[PDB]
Image 1 (cartoon, one colour):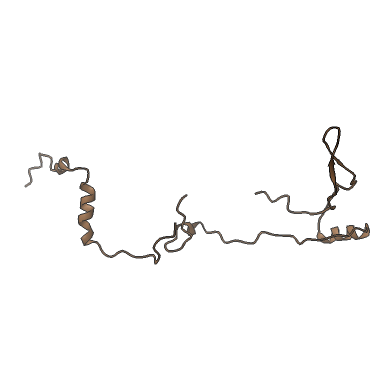
Image 2 (cartoon, each protein chain N blue to C red):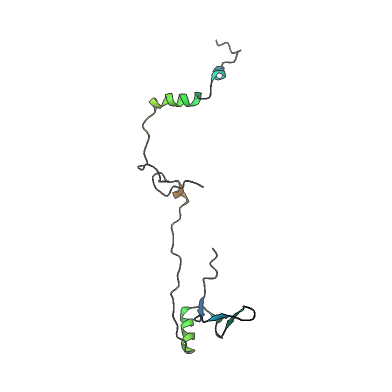
Length: 44
Length: 87
């Protein structure tokens, strides 16, 4: 049985300014190829 | 945007010379018909009125705005140039 008396969500005390966008960069390899609208943009 | 003043036919006369009044600078005229405006319910009524009064006339056809297709959903198109960049 788990201890269930301490707090087990303490990893976030060590996060920094770029934690979110580093995971996003790391996650790019797993993504599936995006769909295309057919144009480079709606032409701005 | 109101369109209420585009519903009746109008008859107006050819514009004539206006000149500066030497005393005050006011706009003077010798044209007794310079302000005459007549309203008609139909083009044919106006034509009939000019002909019996012996006035040469030019008649211009009524202009109606063209019907248009409005789609609020077009502002958010997947792959068309109608997608708006701002709201």
